[PDB]
Amino acid sequence: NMNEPRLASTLRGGLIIEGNVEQRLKPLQIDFYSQMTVDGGGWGTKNYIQDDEWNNLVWEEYLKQIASINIVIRSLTEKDKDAYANTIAFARIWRVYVHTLAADKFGPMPFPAYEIVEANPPYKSLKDIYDEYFRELDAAINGFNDSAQPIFSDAGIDLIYKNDVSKWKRFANSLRLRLAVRLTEVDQEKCIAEANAAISSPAGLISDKADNAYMPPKADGSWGQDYNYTMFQITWSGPICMSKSVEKLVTNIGGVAWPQGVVNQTSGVAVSSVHPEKVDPRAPKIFQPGIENGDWKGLVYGPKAEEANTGIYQSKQCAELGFIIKDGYPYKSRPYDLFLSEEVHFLKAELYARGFIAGDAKSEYEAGVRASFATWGVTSEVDDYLTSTEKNEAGTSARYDDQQGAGNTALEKIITQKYIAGIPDLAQEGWNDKRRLNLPRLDVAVYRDQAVYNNNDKDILKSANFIKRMRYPTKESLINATEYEKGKSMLGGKGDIVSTPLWWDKNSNYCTSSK
């Protein structure tokens, strides 16, 4: 009967924004892997060394949230499937979304079914997991009915769309397009067929800022219930830095000169002479100068833990998060970005540029960049940015027609702009595209787990130099051995380690940067 309070807790719960398990999967893992942000601390995950205690908490939390959504779906379908059709349809969408965050990290894993109560849910291949995604998303879009009860009894309960069914259909369809482009390397036939179904759907996609999916934090004074980057960097005085790789991507590109009055809003220290002459207008709005000396430079990624906060690795002397400060105070109430209209444009832009589907790649590329400059309040700069031939330190320019030079291909432009538009909340999609296309260009970590990596191999064009997955919790090999070995067999290769490429990962390299 009381299924609403259970399904309402899976909204923030499934996304994991409680500042505890969140810290151990977002800033201290997938942020390091995508290099979207770099906490200055001496964490071993920066060197791709797994913390099994963290991975177990992350693994248990996602499956706990999926099981909770399954309790609501199973009880409502049995009680009244026709009357609670809009609640069941939404629950099937959120069940898909939450599981993607788990499956894109660990790979083949359990996907507990809602139809029956599984005593020990079996490990499923990423093929079966992804085939279930599209199947569930398609049925859930057709599941909604205006005659049925609203998603929740109160509109305020739905933190994302406030009971707006049409916006949930757009998000579900945008997720179908996102998971379809994930299969460009492993299965072009399914990638194109699922993307065509997503683009042709009458439900539509996230086509404008009004359709964007956000998750607002509580911001009610409760511990770890804010936009938690504010607690890690400001409250705990731990700089979360811009990476050297991102500095190379945002420098010079767009031709727009460095803006005036750039200061660290925590210490009040103005930007030093250490900053580029020209920079992407979004960069100084995402990252503020170093809290100690005002240097605006990227933190070199992945040195040995004992070298953290020493020499060039001083996080207080590198550019840190700046958008987490609003009106002179910590932006604690900032909603988490789930799916923005920018990504939908770059998803279609990639499919059109690669000749997978017929369409105007340039128009989708520019519409994506313009929506991102609107998101970061720099629309007055987007016209000069898009017409500039100035190349970043990867060799990529913003002008779509200027496809000459190393690192300046059409696909490299799309992924560079898709990556910047996703900083930092879309780190999982940043890590997904880095595994799928080896894009954008990122620096190879100074030190990586020597039991897994050859430190002499720092070729940026080798996708195997970048982490492929997070290891399973080691407790799975002890109390769930039969199913753990099945998951290990599905992974193949060297087994349950960080360097094993996932099903959709063919170690494809589309980076053409010379340096």
Image (cartoon, grey):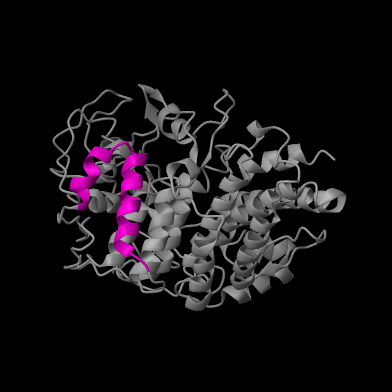
In percent of width and height, residue 410 lies at 27, 66
Q: Quadrant of the C terminus?
A: bottom left
Q: Position of residue 37 (x, y in %)?
A: 38, 46
Of 134 and 121, which appears nearest the observer? 134
Residue lying at 84% horizontally and 49% vertically, measured from the top left: 80
In this orientation, does residue 153 appear? yes
Task: Indicate the quadrant where residue 124 lies.
Answer: bottom right
- Would residue 385 be counted in the magenta stretch? yes
Q: Is residue 122 left or right of 137 when viewed as pictured?
A: right
Between residue 396 and residue 209, name the one nearer to us: 209
x and y percent of residue 511 in the render? Answer: 29, 68
The magenta region covers 359-386
Q: Residue at x 33, y 68 (%)?
A: 353
Q: Is 353 contained in the magenta span? A: no
Q: Residue at x 50, y 78 (%)?
A: 189
Which of the 4 image quadrants contains residue 175? bottom right
Q: Is residue 333 left or right of residue 58?
A: left
Give the residue displayed 64% in from the left and 71% down from the top: 128
Principal SS element in the magenta part?
Answer: helix
Residue 302 seen in the current view: no
Q: Quadrant of the N terminus?
A: top right
On screen, 24 above or below 480?
A: above
Location of residue 396 by image quarter = bottom left
Spot occupied by residue 165 in the image (x, y as percentages of width and height): 62, 46
Q: Is residue 111 above or below residue 71?
A: below
